[PDB]
Image (tube, rainbow, N blue to C red):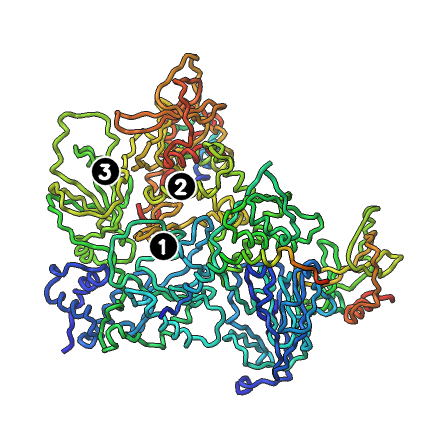
Amino acid sequence: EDVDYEKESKRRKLEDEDFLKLKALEFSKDIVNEK
Amino acid sequence: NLLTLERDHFKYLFLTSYFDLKDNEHVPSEPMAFIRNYLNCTFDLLDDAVLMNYFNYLQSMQLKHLVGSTSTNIFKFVKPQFRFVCDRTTVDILEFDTRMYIKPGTPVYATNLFTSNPRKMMAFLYAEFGKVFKNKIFVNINNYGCVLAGSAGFLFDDAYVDWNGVRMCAAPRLDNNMHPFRLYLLGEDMAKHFVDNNILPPHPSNAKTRKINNSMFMLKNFYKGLPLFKSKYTVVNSTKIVTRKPNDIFNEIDKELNGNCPFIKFIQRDYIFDAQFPPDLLDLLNEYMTKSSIMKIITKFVIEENPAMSGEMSREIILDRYSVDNYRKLYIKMEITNQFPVMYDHESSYIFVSKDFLQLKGTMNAFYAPKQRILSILAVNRLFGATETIDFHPNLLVYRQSSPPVRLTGDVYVVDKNEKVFLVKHVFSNTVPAYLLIRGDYESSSDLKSLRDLNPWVQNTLLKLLIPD
Amino acid sequence: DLLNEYMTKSSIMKIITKFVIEENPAMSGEMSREIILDRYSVDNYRKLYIKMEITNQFPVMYDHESSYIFVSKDFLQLKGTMNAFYAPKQRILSILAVNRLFGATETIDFHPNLLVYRQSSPPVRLTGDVYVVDKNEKVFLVKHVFSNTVPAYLLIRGDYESSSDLKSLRDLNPWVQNTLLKLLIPD
Amino acid sequence: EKYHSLFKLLETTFDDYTCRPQMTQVQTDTLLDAVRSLLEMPSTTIDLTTVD
Amino acid sequence: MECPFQIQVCISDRFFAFPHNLVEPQSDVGNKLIENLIVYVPTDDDRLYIDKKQFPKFNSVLVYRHEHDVNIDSRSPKKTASATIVYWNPLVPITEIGAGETRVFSVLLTNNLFYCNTMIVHHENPKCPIEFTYPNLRPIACEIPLSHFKELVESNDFLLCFNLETSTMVKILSLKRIFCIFQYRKQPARYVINLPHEEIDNLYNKLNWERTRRLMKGDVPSNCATVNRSSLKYIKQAQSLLGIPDYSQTVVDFVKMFQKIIFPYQLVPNVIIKLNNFDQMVSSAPNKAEPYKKIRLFCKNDSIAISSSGIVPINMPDFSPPNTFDYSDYANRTNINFVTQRVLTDGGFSSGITVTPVKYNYYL
């Protein structure tokens, strides 16, 4: 048993280290203008 | 019959209990046996009334941070036993050192409980806190334990812990404990609830088999456990002194250090301010010492040789305020194997003040002399024995008008190219490193030096002394 | 004593707050201690600290009822008025948007001479909704909010020119409208 | 008392003769200090001669 | 202020960008799921960063700029159940609530939100950006980061503006978002602001109160901040009086270097005491003149503590009124004057000499 959260908190830290990457997909030029 | 002991032996009782005894030989045999029983904690064997009397005697010896007490159950259930308030803690500059946030002025208690190891158990305390309150949001639970807006909370922490001192700066650890971490409690309602809870934790560490004491955790009543060890010194001669006058102490110090020994050791025991004490209790305490306690080495600003004044080594001579307010000067046979309070390596000695050298007000390690109109800074050592100070003023720094063909040798550090201020190395009696401030027309073999390239010790002093204010 | 242990859901109730100017950050975490006061006696009062609670019940109230603000001792309420007050240091008249005054012990009768017609300077400009109380007397009302949280309208009299976006008094709330209707005292 | 001392000194003038009292050196000095204090001046060289 | 029931607030630095995932259709009692969704935003430009298609679980999505009504102000906001409602980085009080618990997401704890049901999901950002000042450049738009984030990722020196008409709250919000997004970068960028800043120092005081409001429930982070103008000029003067190998050396380095001395000399560097002195309030407090705010400082396994007044017993106040007093026969005025005259004659000095006795608190 390890009731505490620090393991998952470290997981969050890793995820936040990844978090910036998604923005490129979020905002880069897009294949088509549907309109 | 219940095991019982006389009032007077409370001396031993407290001694052993509170300061983390190691030796057991020199306590009188029967009281020692009784104490052993008590440490075995078989409460049933001992009279309660004895205990209540002892506690009232402790109320007489009015230790400050005692938790108010009303029942013997303090010995038989988890309870707080000392009381504290959150100090300012209001600084941002350095790291939090995992000193988690507390609301300013939060009241605090220390438990009677110590554990070898966190994280194995605290789920139990979590369940208890779940009892204490039903609805909860966003508890700041952590490794150490419950936190919620500070407020209600608890944590394991080491014994001697300061509250709300602004740092935990690095220092070596001396001591060892089976159960290093006492629990501490935050939020008064928790302690209030525990007045009713009247409980002891389950102890599966011992299979819950009704064991008085447990492999991983242990109650102690008011155990502070400060370091201690027996005096063993080969006493040669002694004297006792009663006074409050500091200048008087310095006069005694001078009188003594007209003796030949280069240096004197001096100590102050730490606990002296804690409460009232029986003089007999002080007498017992004298034969033990605390390795953490503050100690100093001090010497005169040695000038020159009296050829007769030599060979004293056999005498080792030391002083301490064995009493809060009184002192017990001692001569002993010079010895190696005797042991003393721990001091960090390379610690500077102290130089006793000279009766014509004036410590700068609000400073250390620096002084001025009038007869030659000179300012002086110790390279390393720390002033001692001053009673009065002179504040710095720039007018003191009279620059010299001397004829231009000046010359100098050794390191020059320019202080101000404009005000023609400089610093140069010197050694008093070819033995004490120091630096000399100077101002005016002066010259060297070029070789300019940068303020960057110097000891922080002198540097901070200079930084204040410039007084850009 | 017996009656104290029951209560009547119809009874008068109010909440009152300070004119919360500013933040003392330490003034926090009190929530657990709810505070109550009532004249349990016809003429004697019970002050209570209680554990903060949800399920306890209190006299029924219409939705959206406005609590009151305790008087600021540096103002005066206006004679025979709610909803409005005056402050001398800045020579300013004030009317609450929706809130309700409490704790005044004395009022000044309004008189028109209180209304400094500041001759001011040829260039003036103002912004936001403005309501011409009187074209002729150069009287205007302007939206304002103290402490980002205290909606109110500011009366003024003077040059105080504004953006073109002049707005009709017809549009305003009945509460303030009636208050102004009296305070004008076209009498 | 830091008044009474001075007060007494000056009251002796009611004897009106120009005889000059002995300086009780210690107390006179402390008295001068008290004078300085009670005059609150920035230590502007208050002196025996001005007292005289 | 009253905080009405039925709201939850989420703080998260991620909320600097809209969390399109997290929202779910609210339903009233009776499972009356409300696929109508209205959102409010600080400004219509903010609408330009939301995709309707992210919400197949929804079927009806609309948004507006928030507006602070007057006529309908209430401690108890207007009720509605026809639509779920959301607010996102709101600046100003809200007057409408949908069916069920409404949720709102922001980076900034306003006073309005204090006594309210809140969740933070905070974490330590280890890295802090480095502030910079200069009398090579690249611009950054002050209004919006979103069209520039990659550049802030891909450079470490920047300068930032404002339009003169900007609302103060907008300034605060923009700055907060700016720093928050910086705190994930790996290289702490240099940055500067093109502003007179006199009030901006008080804006930093606002930031401090905000961090404290956070700390009321927060991560106890190793946050980075300072008083600027006074502290800055003092530190600059100090370094100039000392060797200046780098005019742009990080300020914290000097503190770090001075750390080496603290324990071995068991005493306080003067720099740290002039700090918490130049500070307006966390200080000797020029706001109030509070010299008694001495620091108590402590170290591992101490039986003792250190202060501006020197050694003290652990967990004790400054000094005991009863004492081994500074018995006044020593430091007697008379003796003091005696010695002072001796000194003066030895020096041949006219003026400017002053002296004082030493004193002790408990330890001596």
Instruction: Inspect the image, locate mark 3, and give the three-letter code of the amino acid beneath it.
Output: Ile
User: Can you say which quadrant of the picture contains the N terminus of chain B?
Assistant: bottom left
Q: How many marks?
A: 3
* SS under mark 1: loop
- For this view, does B191 lie left or right of residue B41? right
The answer for which chain carries disc 3 is B
* SS under mark 3: helix
- Residue at the location (69% across, 66% down)? E63
Whether residue B248 can be seen here: no
In the rendering, at what x and y percent does residue E185 appear?
52, 51
Q: In the figure, E70 relative to B97: above or below? A: below
Dot label at residue E258: 2
User: Is there a contact, CB below 8 Å, between mark 2 and mark 3?
Assistant: no
- Residue at the location (27% across, 54% down)? B271
Q: Nearer the viewer, residue E183 or E194?
A: E183
* SS under mark 2: helix
